[PDB]
Amino acid sequence: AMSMAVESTGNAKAEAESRAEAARIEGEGSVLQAKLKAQALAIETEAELE
Amino acid sequence: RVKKVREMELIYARAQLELEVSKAQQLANVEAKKFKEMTEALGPGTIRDLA
């Protein structure tokens, strides 16, 4: 029982930390997409402003 | 981005403001002094009988 218990806990922490680390860096990805697509829209309509 | 373009729509609408303003303003001067001279050259009793 405890054998396949640690089996199951690791086996699910597997498909867990997978999507988890993917989430980490897809998130910091959108973080800099934010900082950037900011300066995109921020000055598109700064020239179009004028 | 939105701030700058719409603060400009501010200045542009200030412009379009003054355009419509003096548009109707001097159209008003037009028609008002039109009917001014109309009824003044008419005369009080003349227009009274005409109506």
Image (cartoon, grey):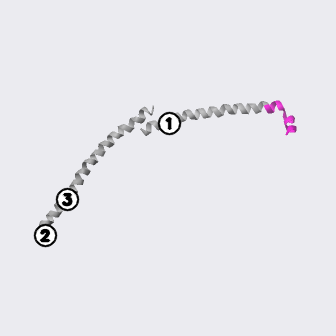
* Spatial CA span between label 3 and label 2: 18 Å
| Residue at (86% x, 37% y) in the render | B50
* Spatial CA span between label 1 and label 3: 55 Å
Marks 1 and 3 close (CB-CB < 8 Å): no
Local packing at callout 2 (Cα closer than 10 Å; few below 14, some 14-19, many 20+) is few
Residue B43 x, y percent position in the rendering: 84, 32
Of mark 3 and mark 2, the one earlier in the sequence is 2
Out of A8 and A47, give the one closest to the viewer.
A8
Range of magenta residues = B38-51
Which residue in the structure is indicated by mark 1?
B9
Residue B29 x, y percent position in the rendering: 70, 31
Q: Tell me, for residue A11, which label it has, or none.
A: none
Co-location on one chain, circles 1 and 3: no
Q: Chain of mark 3?
A: A
SS class of the residue under badge 3? helix
Which residue in the structure is indicated by mark 2?
A1
Q: Which amino acid does the dot numbered 1 rest on?
A: Glu
Which residue in the structure is indicated by mark 3?
A13
